[PDB]
Each structure stands twice: as C-alpha cells, then as structure tokens.
Image (tube, rainbow, N blue to C red; front, side):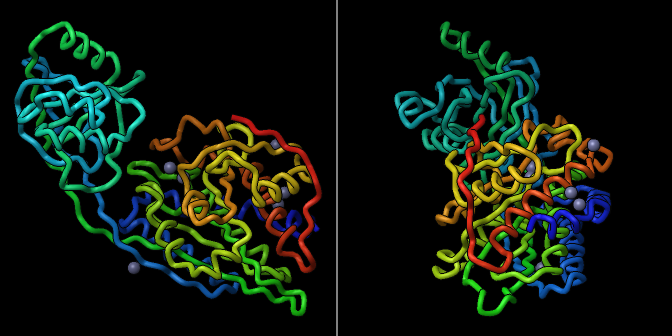
Length: 412
Ligand SMILES: [Zn+2]
Ligand SMILES: [Zn+2]
Ligand SMILES: [Zn+2]
Ligand SMILES: [Zn+2]
Ligand SMILES: [Zn+2]
Ligand SMILES: [Zn+2]
C-alpha cells in the first residue's frame, strides 16, 4: 500500500512550492500572507479540490520605533515584548522576584518600575501582576545569555510598557537592590501600535469515494502559511505547506474511504490563531469523527536533525501509532516526544488525536532571515511526504483500518 504514496511523492513539486512562497516573509495578516493564501488555494484547485477560505480577525502588533532603557544615567540594551504599551516614565526601580501575585503584593510599586526575573509564569502575568500594583513599567531579565525576546501573548490595556534584558545585566541590578541600593530607571517605549488584521485558513477537502467501504472517519493534515517578521520562512513553514499540497495531489489519484482535510493555517506564529479559529468551527460530530490530525511544521531543512513526532501530553495516540507504523516500513524507528508550539495543539485541545512532525533539533536558521530556500533538502521533504502520506493512507485506503503492534521510544 505504501507504494501508492512513495511512487508519487514529487520532491520537485514541493521544492517549487517553497521557492514561490519564500521569496519574502509572510507575516500574518499582511499582503504577502494573502498572496500565499491565493497561491495555496489555486494549487489545491489544480489538483481538483473544492477549496474554502476561512477569514478571521486578530490584533496585530507593530514593534516600537524607540526602545530607550536607562539605569540612572547609563543606557542599557533592552527589547520591548510584543504587545507592549508605550511609556515615558522615570522612577525608582523595585525588585519583585518572579512577579507573582504575592511577590508584588507586599511591595510598594505605585508609580514605580518593576524589575522582574524570568521564571515559570508567563511574561503576561508578570506585567499584569505588577501593573495591578501601580507599576508604570516593567523590566524583565533573562535566565540565559543573549537578548530576551518574548511576547505578552496578545493585546491587553491592563498592561504597561515591558522590556526585556539579558541575565547578566539583570542579576546585577537585582543584587544591588537586594544589597539595599536605591536605583532609578527610565523606560520609554514609542512607536508601538496595535491594529486589527485579517488572516485566513485554506481548507481543501476530499470526500470519501470508495462506496460501500466508506467510513465516516476524518483525518486532517495541516501546516501554517505565515512566517515571522524578516524570515522568508522556507522551512518554517513553507516546507509543511509544500508537503501538505503534494500529499493532497497524491491522494487525488487514489480512492479513499476516509474524508481528508488538507489545511494551511494563518497566523500560527501569533499564537496559533488560525488553527484555533478552524477548530472552533467544528461540530461535535466532526470532532468525534476526526481520528487524527497530522501537523507538518519544519520538515525540509538539510541543517535540522532526525524526524520526530511530538504530542502535547507526551503520550502516544493514533497519529503517532500510524506515523511509527509507516516509518517502520519505510525508514526505521520514528521516536515521539512532548511538545506543543504548533497547530496540533489546537486539535489536541478538542480531544482529537494529534501530532507534530518535525526535524529536531531544529536548524540554527529558525526564525531568522537565513530561513531560506538554499537550506532545503528535497530528500528530506520526500521522506516526510512518504512517511506522513503512508501513515494517512494506512487509514484512508479502502478497507478496515488495522494498526499492527510495534514499539517506538519516547525521546526528549
Ligand atoms: Zn520517497
Ligand atoms: Zn517521492
Ligand atoms: Zn479575506
Ligand atoms: Zn512553524
Ligand atoms: Zn515559527
Ligand atoms: Zn541523500
């Protein structure tokens, strides 16, 4: 059965998809993401699919033009978190540990700037908790080297300007404050702005066409078509889009007894907005009938590691069982691990078996201007299409689904 897939997976087709999409970054809600949506829609149509485009709005964020952070007089290096409000405050700096509801409680922060350490709770909770006590601004310092780049999740007027700084420059301030030093700081954020944008999900569905063998099962194969600012996103995630499109083309040449939904989600980098919006469109019957959701994200980099399957809870499910079965016949042992950070999380949330297929550890070009076409491996793209396609086909081919018992290890 695998041969029906493996003899049809065209690596050149996938390479070409990536070439077209990665000519420029595809920031969610931008003209470039719209261009990708149109392109993807047209390719699905070319394979004979009826296509639907689901629109949705979300709050976008334009990084601030001026990020000035100063400790008394010396100018420091800091980066405002996404969705950070604007500010022009100069006041005493107060250390509030991790910034929990208790840490900031027993401390006078009214009109002051809070110094918080990165820990477990979200950057959003810290800013929010500090702002609740009167803090006019928040300075968060990293736990490791390198600049601290984070996001407050989404817009929220309850926030106050928030900027991040490296661990070294943070432990120093915290130490002096604990030592009893009275420090004054300056936090000025200008340029930041939030506006409503529209993104889209592209859905191509192949209804079962066997006949008496048709089941009422549904399988979703997805990827996301947006990329981060300044990143051409060849591997993240044009690669996933490419495999999604090619597998749709491959399946159009075969009879199936399972409904297949090939989807490219928008605004994945903004917090899985697209997939959340699509998941929310499903009926209770559709949810119970979806036997598995396969997410393809970063599956073609010559500089990435081996293929692995990630689940939200780090447990095996129907999708990892199918992935492992296919791989066992085609390439060898395919491990699984625990990780979210992609659209499969939106389906796992509904109780639908889901897994992310990705090459880990990821390449160093991840989310950089270096995530380009010349880093792509046709051989790897073809391998992923072969494995994911055969895993899906094990279920979609006419006849009852049978998954033989096979062992595969969990790997972190
Ligand atoms: Zn192959
Ligand atoms: Zn092939
Ligand atoms: Zn639209
Ligand atoms: Zn991605
Ligand atoms: Zn990404
Ligand atoms: Zn080779």
